[PDB]
Each structure stands twice: as structure tokens, then as C-alpha cells.
Image (tube, helix red, strand yellow):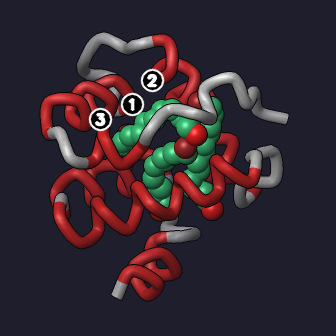
Amino acid sequence: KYTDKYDNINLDEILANKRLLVAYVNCVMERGKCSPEGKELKEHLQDAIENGCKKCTENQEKGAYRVIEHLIKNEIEIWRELTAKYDPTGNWRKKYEDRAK
Ligand SMILES: OCCCCCCCCCCCCBr
Ligand SMILES: OCCCCCCCCCCCCBr
Ligand SMILES: OCCCCCCCCCCCCBr
């Protein structure tokens, strides 16, 4: 089971501040420095894609959808690079895009 120690981080504040959001994106894309939380996310994202969040907490599932919907609607280029890197066979791309729409 993934740790819940970072589960009280306010995702709304991150999504509303481009500088904060880009820091996490560059970390997960393996082109920028990581915060402790960013490193933890980077280290579990591939696994979560392979098993549909089987080890995610309820807060992580809810938070993943919040972040993903925001990217699909407002940061298309970021969404595309993330899904291409972590989900190259497209297990979830159409499913999340359909929900967002
Ligand atoms: O439940 C919250 C734990 C994860 C803490 C990191 C939040 C990062 C959210 C921004 C992700 C941007 C796409 Br890489
Ligand atoms: O259905 C595929 C899920 C895609 C999003 C997975 C988010 C994984 C969150 C990992 C949290 C680790 C603590 Br920082
Ligand atoms: O095709 C699926 C690609 C999934 C990439 C989205 C990663 C965003 C995860 C954010 C984690 C937040 C949980 Br608090």
C-alpha cells in the first residue's frame, strides 16, 4: 500500500500556481529536481498505471482524477507528455479523456 503521509497536501493550491505545478511535472518527467513528495509520486506512478491504482489510498484516487482532469482541460501539452511517457500503450488515455469531456 502506498504511504498516506503526504495525503493532506492541498492539490487545489498546486493546480492554481503554474510554478508549483511545473516543479512536480519536471520532476516526474525526469528533467528537474524533485521535492520529497514529487520523488514519491515519480517512484510509484508506473506501478499505479500497471494495476489501476490497486495500492492507492482513496484520497490518492480522488486526487489523481482531479489532477488528470485539470491537465486534460487546461494543460494539454503536459497531459500528452505524461501519458506518452508513463502509459505508452494507452491503457488509460481514452478512459480519462472521456471522463474529462
Ligand atoms: O495525495 C497527494 C500525494 C501526492 C503529492 C504530490 C502532488 C503532486 C500533484 C501534481 C502532479 C502533476 C503531474 Br506530475
Ligand atoms: O488508473 C491509473 C491511475 C493513474 C494515476 C495514478 C496515481 C498514483 C499516485 C501515487 C501516490 C504515491 C504517493 Br506520493
Ligand atoms: O494515461 C494515464 C496517464 C496518467 C498520468 C497522470 C499522473 C498524475 C498523477 C497525480 C497524482 C495525484 C494523487 Br494525489
For image coordinates 62% across by 35% down, the residue present is: 7
Which element type, helix, strand or loop, lies under badge 1?
helix
Residue type, numbered disc 1: Val
Q: Which residue is mark 3?
A: 25
For marks 1 and 3, give the CA distance. 5 Å
Circle 2 residues within 10 Å: few <14, some 14–19, many ≥20: some
Which amino acid type is shown beneath numbered disc 2?
Gly
Q: Are marks 1 and 3 in contact (CB under 8 Å)?
A: yes
Number of numbered callouts drawn: 3
Residue at the image position 76 percent from the left and 46 percent from the top: 57
Quick check: 31 left or right of 30?
left
Secondary structure state at the residue bearing disc 2: helix
Q: Is residue 4 left or right of residue 18?
A: right
Q: Nearer the viewer, residue 26 or 50?
A: 26
Q: Nearer the viewer, residue 10 or 28?
A: 10
Q: Which residue is mark 1?
A: 28
Residue occupying the point 17% across, 39% down: 17
From what the image shows, is residue 13 above or below residue 62?
above
Q: Is mark 2 within 8 Å of ligand 1?
A: yes
The reply to whether callout 1 and callout 2 are in contact (CB within 8 Å) is yes
